[PDB]
Length: 164
Image 1 (cartoon, helix red, strand yellow):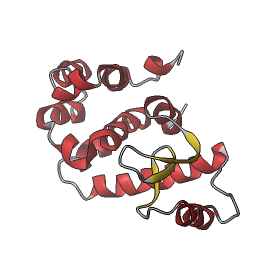
Image 2 (image 1 turned 45 degrees about the horizontal axis):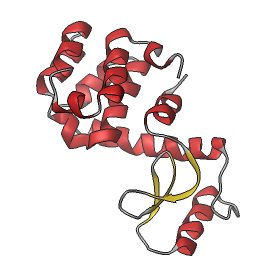
Image 3 (image 1 turned 90 degrees about the vertical axis):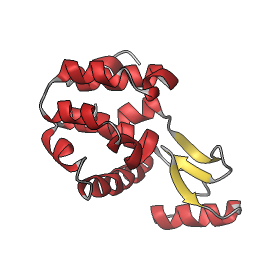
């Protein structure tokens, strides 16, 4: 399992163009196509991105391609972020997925807020970090997702996602 699978489960994968909460044309795992109100413009952007005639429908593999670009852009930001940089730098691959997961959820700025949690994570105090994370506002609002993410930080495995 990789990052794609974790997010496919927490956020959801859509193979046909859809509108998000706000009305924007999206696809894959929350991959924004365009802020234009046109379905055609949306399809046009997809074909560009794919490099082929899709008519608004992609394969899993393709979505994965897009998800990775999205992931790269997130990381690039992380790496220009003093508080986040050393933590990401310090985590293993699995654990890096969990952090990304958070970024995707609440943005770069929201995660930067977990001052302490972050400190513990960079120090490999997994449990304390998990304890710490559970006091957030985030943990109370999206508790299923948050439990799964914390469990990943705590164990360094995909156990939370095993039978999903």
